[PDB]
Image: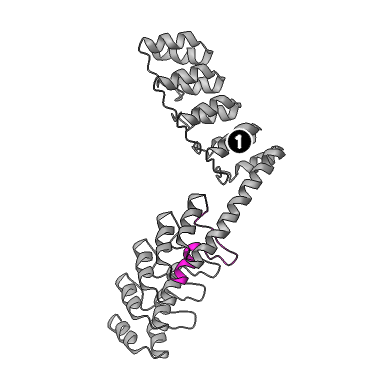
């Protein structure tokens, strides 16, 4: 019974009653049938004093209702700026998503709460977050005619695109500290250039081992395909970067991936004379019988190109 009274007092804005109920043992994190806590209801109705009292007494700032909405979602939707600021100060998750993929920034942008948008952005909100329909917050601002917010979010996305371009260049050039700084300031490790090369492609091609490792640790797709089907492992096998081959395989690289010509990493290592790489690829399950579009196996290429030691290794594995 205490829990129900606290929910109602919080919803009704009964500041004195909230304090008494808490003093008498009401559970600050009690939840109604749909998972709303007193903090949800105070944030939704705009009762700043009660929000602060609930947080002072142990309220879970990131409590989820049964569909994933947090108190920050509700304050962002209803446009309660000071409550947004208090929630964030008490640890609210600025990028939390409900079961539809909707984050607080989606709601502030859709419902035209500019100062809340600006506060969410200052607190780390992700302008690239897409809901289940594929909408970013900018998309919703545009669709709903909130042009000032749309323009603000467009500028923010253009700054991230610039960071993405610098990340490609730093990864190609081997500037490790620049790579790490760019990732920390929000560069997308899975960005790709016009031909489909990602930072991981460029680092593997240029033999930048440390950068390969940093990119994979920050979530880079080990099996990303460029526009012709080449993966990072293709490029490391071609250029002969043995340690990078081993890191890629350790991180899940597909050992038998083929480009649009049917060329696999083993073809490239055998053709270009990289014996240790051939051996590592065989150890990880490379397919000696794979034929490219010309009908050539890796053994065929080793024979055609005079790589006798490799030809013998591949016959042993026939």
Picture quadrant where residue 241 is located: bottom left
Front in this rendered view, residue 92 or 78: 92
- Quarter of the picture containing the N terminus is top left
Picture quadrant where residue 5 is located: top left
Q: Is residue 69 above or below residue 136?
A: above
Front in this rendered view, residue 21 or 135: 21
Tell me the residue at 48%/50% (across/down): 184
Picture quadrant where residue 103 is located: top right
Image coords of residue 285 (percent x, y): 32, 70
Image coords of residue 233 (percent x, y): 42, 69
Image coords of residue 125 (percent x, y): 54, 40
Tell me the residue at 34%/81% (across/down): 275
Q: Which residue is mark 1?
A: 117
- Quarter of the picture containing the C terminus is bottom left
Front in this rendered view, residue 15 or 85: 85
The magenta stretch spans residue 126: no
Front in this rendered view, residue 57 or 78: 57
Image coords of residue 238 (percent x, y): 44, 76
Residue extending furthest toward the left: 316
Left/right placement of residue 3 relative to residue 45 reads left
Magenta residues, dominant SS class: loop
Q: Is residue 40 above or below residue 132?
A: above
- Disc tally is 1
Tell me the residue at 41%/8% (across/down): 20
Is residue 1 at least partly visible in the picture? no
Left/right placement of residue 227 relative to residue 214 reads right
Query: Tag 1, which secondary structure?
Result: helix
Q: Is residue 121 above or below residue 205?
A: above
Residue density around tag 1, few if under 14, some if 14–19, many if 20 or more, within 10 Å: many
**Stretch of the chain drawn in magenta:** 186-207
The magenta stretch spans residue 195: yes
């Amino acid at each position: 019974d205490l829990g129900k009274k606290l929910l109602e007092a919080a919803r009704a804005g009964q500041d004195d009653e909230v304090r008494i109920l808490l003093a008498n043992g009401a559970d600050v994190n009690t939840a109604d049938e749909t998972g709303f806590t007193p903090l949800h209801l105070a944030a939704w109705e705009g009762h700043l004093g009660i929000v602060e009292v609930l947080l002072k007494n142990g309220a879970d700032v990131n409590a989820n209702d049964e569909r994933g909405h947090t108190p920050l979602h509700l304050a962002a939707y209803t446009g309660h700026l000071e409550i947004v600021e208090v929630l964030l100060k008490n640890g609210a998750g600025v990028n939390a998503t409900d079961v539809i993929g909707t984050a607080p920034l989606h709601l502030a942008a859709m419902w035209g709460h500019l100062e809340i948008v600006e506060v969410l952005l200052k607190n780390g909100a992700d302008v690239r977050a897409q809901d289940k329909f594929g909408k970013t917050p900018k998309d919703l601002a545009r669709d709903n005619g909130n042009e000032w917010i749309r323009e603000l979010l467009e500028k923010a996305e253009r700054k991230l695109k610039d960071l993405d371009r610098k990340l490609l260049e730093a990864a190609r050039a081997g500037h490790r500290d620049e790579v790490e700084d760019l990732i920390k300031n929000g560069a997308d490790v899975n960005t790709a250039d016009e031909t489909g090369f990602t930072p991981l492609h460029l680092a593997a091609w240029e033999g930048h081992l440390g950068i390969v490792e940093v990119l994979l640790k920050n979530g880079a797709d080990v099996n990303a395909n460029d526009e012709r089907g080449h993966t990072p492992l293709h490029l490391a096998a071609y250029t002969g970067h043995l340690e990078i081959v081993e890191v890629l395989l350790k991180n899940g690289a597909g050992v038998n991936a083929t480009d649009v010509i049917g060329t696999a990493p083993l073809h490239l290592a055998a053709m270009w004379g990289h014996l240790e790489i051939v051996e590592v690829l065989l150890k990880h399950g490379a397919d000696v019988n794979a034929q490219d579009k010309f009908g050539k196996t890796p053994f065929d290429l080793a024979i055609d190109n005079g790589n006798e030691d490799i030809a013998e290794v591949l016959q042993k594995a026939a």
